[PDB]
Length: 298
Image 1 (cartoon, rainbow, N blue to C red):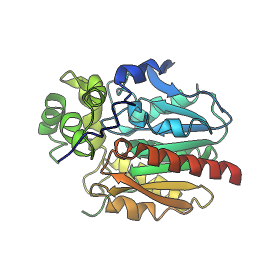
Image 2: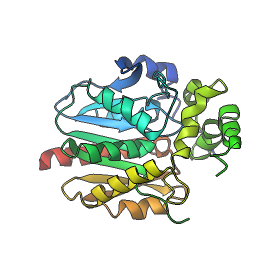
Image 3: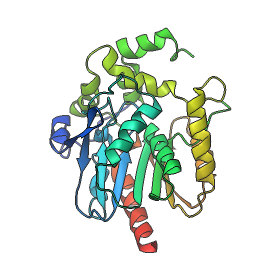
Image 4: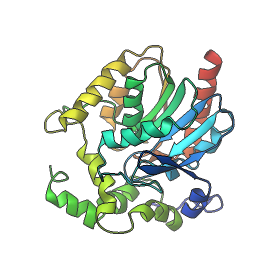
């Protein structure tokens, strides 16, 4: 049985409160909603959420890192309070198109630090592969580290029903993979972008449909993941931090995959999948110390 954190309401940040702290920037034919801590712009730490969530996910993690580096946190296209995709497509490369265009408008330093979760990690990994000179360090967790060989309906018409009609990922999966019980306002912040039925929920269906299954998975995504996996396995000069979820959720293949990447520090924190909601401060402190060590080592 899940229970509320009894100290959490006193520091709760509602959706409206978070969105009031964000800015909007035009990007290609749309716009991106994002948080930007602004100060210490000699460095940039870019935090990337994955399916079902938004920049809101990182709200209690980022304050720990802000004093060491500029922190930038987008809502991915079609998610959070960001604009929608010009053609209504939300595959990995659609997200990447808008993300990379946004990066060009941010006045980033030559080398950037990424923090990725879920498909947010895949975006960071793909960016790294295609910009090998622009990466200072990478932190990842519950991430798309490799293709899946070992261990249908979502891709079927029922999947459209499950998600567009029944909101499966936001209303069934999300709360099931948080160990605590979310405050009502906190869940409401995740529901808001996807409160209405139909096409507005597309990104939450398109993400799982990108799954890099060798047998049956989108061939272009399988190749993207193979490519960045090989690069990451050879990236001895690239410092990495892997945050392992305890107990996690079916997370063993993530951990063994993560261990194939050289120059990785390993830490562990409480959680299932959305560990930011169960151990944000522990995560923030680990990330802070890692970043500090990376910058001193330079």
